[PDB]
Image (cartoon, rainbow, N blue to C red; front, top):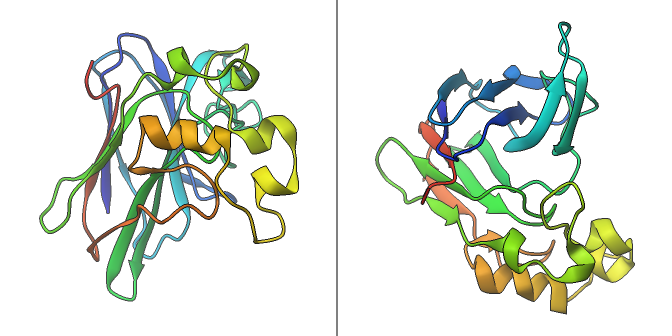
Length: 207
């Protein structure tokens, strides 16, 4: 499947794409404002994620650091990134269907739209000013708004027992972005698309 990743933010982001144990395509790339990066993702990919990283410094060899979303210091992400990261998540060709969602479960750093470019389903978006409005205890100094599990490491926020409810913190993400997951057991905002759809991820869609 084809993903076009578009940086509509006025600032540079470093896009990342991974399925947790492997890069998707090149795994990451700098996107200046307006730049678009087209990647190919193998059919059947389960548990892929795309995210933006902010304020990265890399050297010749692709090693460095980002203030949000860093994936072990690599330009080309092999693993997932450090919160806070707004997440585009997808599982492709699962019994004939693609499944996509946006998640604030690992916090929020950049606004995002995640839409099909082919027919038969709708897109989802989380484009509210979650960083500006972020509760004081969840603000990340690097930028971004952490989720409560990252910050506090409790069974309730991390849903470690498989039982947990919404919290003051999850409701904040949910109030600003109803179409994104706000905690592990949120009512699913997953969208079902035809198998083998293609997609566009736009950072800062309303910029």
